[PDB]
Amino acid sequence: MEELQDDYEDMMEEN
Image (cartoon, rainbow, N blue to C red; front, side, top):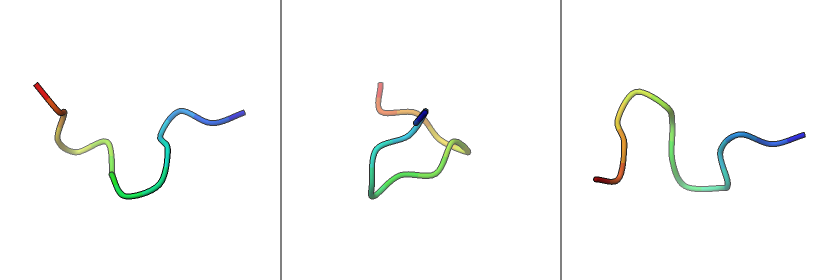
């Protein structure tokens, strides 16, 4: 059960 992968943090978004 993962939302995010590895090198990220859901306080930004890769648009």
